Image (cartoon, rainbow, N blue to C red; front, side, top):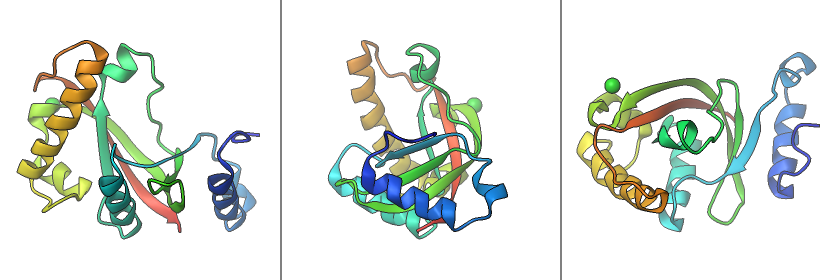
Length: 159
Ligand SMILES: [Cl-]
């Protein structure tokens, strides 16, 4: 009932996970999606694998999407089928926490949880400033370092 329109490969994979847990556990889930991470093939595929392996355990996005563009906030307990660029399911993640912080207040520990490149805050900054500047242009605003982010932490539950 909750994900009839999901792309078939990812729907099948998600059904495998739900069937591999007890009815009590599967029936609690109410929020589902299927997507890749990032905006390019190289990083989508690297990130799916980092997530698979437990190296990438967090992500973030501009809060502007939710407060101004009306996107639904991420929820604890959400399941995402993590695909590669080409839509092949790689793993399933469950959101474990959601919070907010300014871009310029992102910590070294959060950058390390995101797990990309050398895990440093400098690498995290270079990557995110670029990506968020592009999104901001399409949104019709300029990126500022004081903008709020939505931080998500998550865990692998299936692969
Ligand atoms: Cl903050």
